Image (cartoon, rainbow over all chains, first blue to last red; front, top):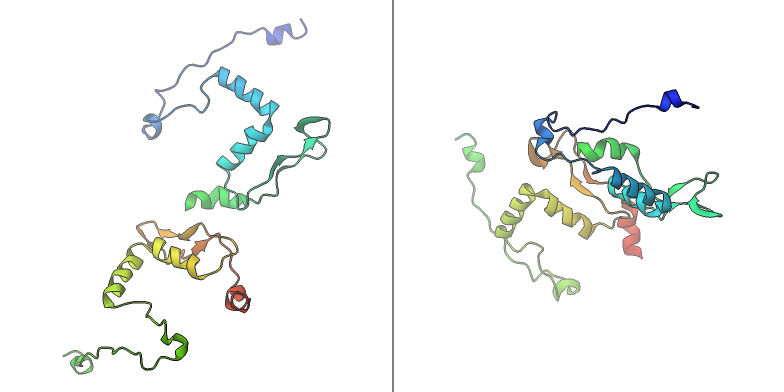
Length: 106
Length: 106
């Protein structure tokens, strides 16, 4: 059709890998997302309310010097983040080098 | 011997002083360390785990603008403080003048 050639392909499922794990993780390896169904529900949450999805991951994985007050600046017409006045983690402070090196080196 | 002359001396114990106290402290004076046995146990703790000994005194006697996260950077081979990368009270903030003057003047 209009791209019928390009898109007319078979879907390839992903096979589990256990036999390529190195001893370092062989005893505890587990994927961060369990399946498509978690992607789907998590994605939904990420779009519908970023305030919680990013809000939490932002403090769980980054080491802040000063906590932030607002996850994002909303668009007046909708609860989604604004393009023109895009800003996140307002009023917090964070040093990239700290998170990249010192956090682990120490 | 090898310094037998120099070191061959009598030990002089310290005598209590109460009769040289001024009225200002005469009613409440008490030494900060009670005896050699406290020196000995406290010293032991100071060497074995500085994290607590200095860690606490650091916040009890200095007025911090921002609390610190780490008492010190350890030596990879031992729990003691590193000479080459010596640093203490990491990530806190402290103004020396504040502690020297304003803290008391106010």
